[PDB]
Length: 178
Ligand SMILES: [Zn+2]
Ligand SMILES: [Zn+2]
Ligand SMILES: [Zn+2]
Image (cartoon, rainbow, N blue to C red; front, side, top):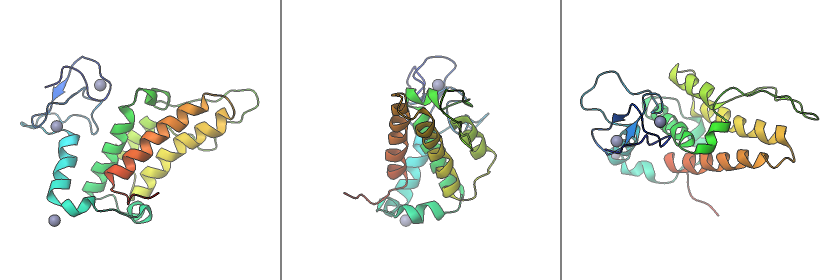
């Protein structure tokens, strides 16, 4: 197994995957690493297993179809992985915890959103469709772009949103387009 956390890349109290070499802090893994279970498979392993069980799940899809899907256990997992992949980027640290807004010439967003809030929402099963998860994810970056305006700090929003969108297309097998 790896000696660092796959998500944050630090050492510490790590839990090791029994089916691949990745390791996780308890709360870096989404969902949080499970109390017992021997062996234990990580979320990278569980996502691979869905794909292997239905190779046609990697033929292309329409985003509109994807969003209307109900949050049954496989869609739930896939959003928990998408979220995980965003937290793998160190720049996710700017979007993790609840923000606040006090900048001359800007008003704060009507509906603030942050990654830990999206994490809690998933955990408490508050999304019924993929749509709900993907709207909040996108809201994070949109709020950021609107608030920081012409400041160069807006670019962090663009960057982390590009990580979200590439990963969403991949995980949900969106049909490739030019
Ligand atoms: Zn970690
Ligand atoms: Zn694994
Ligand atoms: Zn099949």
